[PDB]
Length: 88
Picture 1: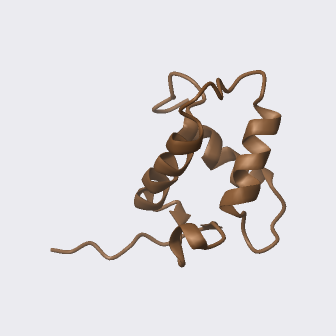
Picture 2: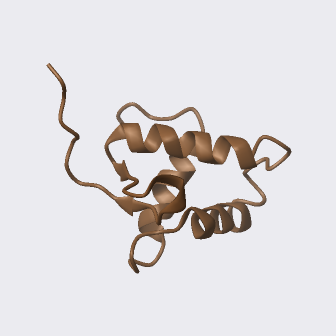
């Protein structure tokens, strides 16, 4: 894999869980967290820094360009397919 991740980190899991979920109207920050914690229960540590880092990793995802957050945290996460305007 090109630029392969060392492991399935938050950024990686949040990414893949999104398409793996039903189209719907995207994937809620709620449902995404529910999916990853449930599915990756025997893989994701979920020791203590899950709740905080989950959202923090989502912040990386929105900056990434792949994830879009129209209404931000109080908004259902949606897949983006257009890079945000780069300020010269």
